Picture 1: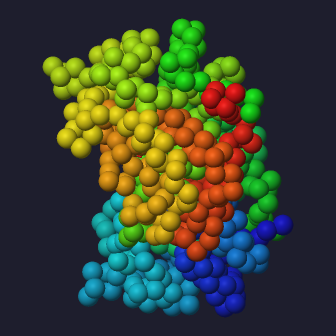
Picture 2: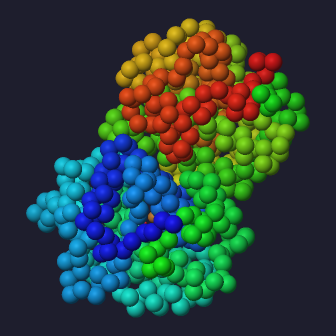
Length: 286
Length: 287
Ligand SMILES: O=c1cc(CO)occ1O
Ligand SMILES: O=c1cc(CO)occ1O
Ligand SMILES: [Cu+2]
Ligand SMILES: [Cu+2]
Ligand SMILES: [Cu+2]
Ligand SMILES: [Cu+2]
């Protein structure tokens, strides 16, 4: 009974109220908690030595961010019980000749691309320099949100609808050894390591700026719209393959199994395995 | 009130073995590293950004943050053995000894001894010596062995004394503005050890050395938890003495420091842990 809408379906009042709430959460000090949580989990390797971490590059990538978004939406509701977390359906923006012309980058919502005169500092929209302070990898101020759409040779474009459809065909949620090299794995496909960077990883590299590296990515509010779409694609996968379940169920690295606590919380993947039990739904499901 | 935390020197040889056993299990399962990471992450979480205050140190939440830290750690201990509690290292009595390194807490059956200067002060005795206990660095990667170097600093050659503890218990205010290292007439800042620092809590970290000598890696040494168990005991004694003093600030402090603000990286507030008896544990001196 909580509907999360496509960004392009939002009214100008819904767009304004969401932007308003994020700014309030930022002013109170709640927003920075989520930046720090995401950076801390990126450093928590499972197990130490491997390149698996609690939030990425392993089987917990999807449930971790679902819990991440769940906690964020609850904090949104503390200020306004009418604001939900919209999702950025970037696979349809990619259909455009110039995806940077999408209304999600308008001055009334997320703001536009970075200014190459000012080292790609974003100077338009509610999160422009002077209105929205960022923190660096070390937790100290860094002086402004940056973006540089499609300025990389490994991610010049946004993922397509065909990329999403081909990932939904995968039968297994994940496969051993539950990491960057997992083949025939929906998790690793959606994450974007199969001929990477694609999908989730490509979207981060396409936006650039803080969004292009793990420890600083949540500095951009579009991080939450991005992962709201990733969580939707996962929820669609769970509906299609109704008789598949999370993997691994056991004997994976600690923090990756079905009932292990996900650092930095005690929440397990099972606790968030059914998003309707969490109290929200995506508009395409109705 | 139904769970007693004993002085380390009062433990039986069976209690010492079970505690060491449980900690090793928590390390093997992967739970122990969660506390290293939690402590490092909170040390980087400045409140507010720019200021010299973090969620776990250098401000009013220092004491309740570590109490919740110890509470969560003790619960994980009970999941493996529902009869093991968190003992405390009463370092104010070890300081009375001429050489505190001769204390039974550093025996091969418990914490092990001082570092070996031949091996760059790697600890080579006890259950946590190199080869039986792997450590992680500030970045979350293995670092290859616990180090200790007792009293090797010019600013903290000795352990704090009994008189240091008594003089801290005299302070009337829990904390004072601006709720940080410069707070004067503050029990919290006094106990932390920034009044003519390093003293008390801060001095103990500097005296042990090794990983214990810097914030992000300190929990790599299991004595980190025994140390803070004693800090939590002294606070609980202060709360009993000054029964009508309360946490400060109650409001209009930096977010994360007020009585009902969530303490990163949890949602726990200082009020949630303000009464340690309600949390389910008690110190043996209270009996
Ligand atoms: O912040 C991130 C950036 C990238 C780019 O690969 O991937 C994953 C992230 O969480
Ligand atoms: O973990 C810590 C390490 C040091 C070293 O001085 O001081 C204070 C701490 O809380
Ligand atoms: Cu992430
Ligand atoms: Cu991401
Ligand atoms: Cu600490
Ligand atoms: Cu300490």
